[PDB]
Length: 393
Length: 52
Image (cartoon, rainbow over all chains, first blue to last red):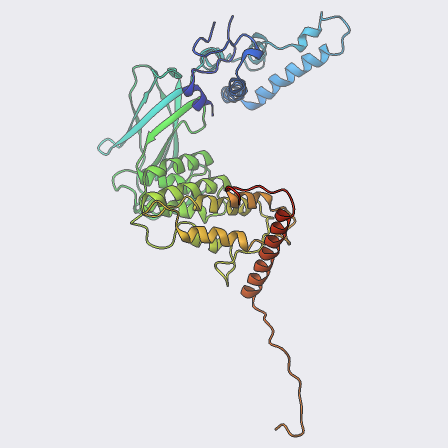
């Protein structure tokens, strides 16, 4: 939301100094002259910058800062002196930074100078190349700092590389003149023997390594995984790396960004990846709800190649319909709250299917109308208004 | 085998889940269509098309 708004119009400036922001058509000196979208993005950017301050100075020290502010205010709140002490209930920026420096011993003045006083987000364009001879991974990260909303980042940058030997984090120092970052790569001895490949968490899984390159061990790369800067990343992986990142990652933001990047690769391996995500309980439900729409877009792009039925129809009849009647939907029992959301989002994405003539097929429209006719809600303890409203959608 | 002995018969029962779902669905759709057409005809009405 904030990178869309700041690249759209100028930027949000937390803590201005009194104009400080002349790129935008109102004055930021008073709350009653702000646009309402600017007020909303102001609150949004403020809580993300506080998450960044928690990233630099750990969460227990952050809660100690907040407790110190509240305790000064509550010793202030019981005095009777007319504001000799009632102004300890008012916080400022300098007092907040001083309380942070009191509890931690680190000051955050570079982070405050970059993300508060400066009003911009950063844009990262990354591309890699694997050097087989020296066994290194040559990243190439360049910033677009000449757009109207952008600024230049010179700090450190975390990158997480999943190779066959596991998941390794690397810190890159991205100075102004930097372009190529050579990080080292590990072995490929988990392709010699079939062993399980260890993940970002402690677990390990069986991966189908037939799509991987023979010479490179690395399975996927993520630039800034923890969202530790206010950034927009445009990484150029290979399509099998996006499919491996969709399947076997233990991070929902990486599964979402792989869904978002698989729309450019309409190959049938990506259709298999999104269909395996859709069938998979123990995936987070908002990833499957995105995979519905991604599968609809991919299915629209590979018409005159699609083999069987329309997308997600057989999957809908496998998950939510009767075993004896495929075209009759099961009676509504909405007590699971994840297959309820997936059930009410799957025909909405299924209706975006189009034939070679650019008209929605009469197999999906008939399916949606049979979902509407055979709807029986006399048996669940929950209402049907959102599911029926999504059927109209 | 019929002169002196008699046993009763019953009507054919339709215990099929498919046709029971179809019967309940079509009866619900027909009664709600009849109700909404009756209530739109005996009151103030709107129309998506001109004089419809």
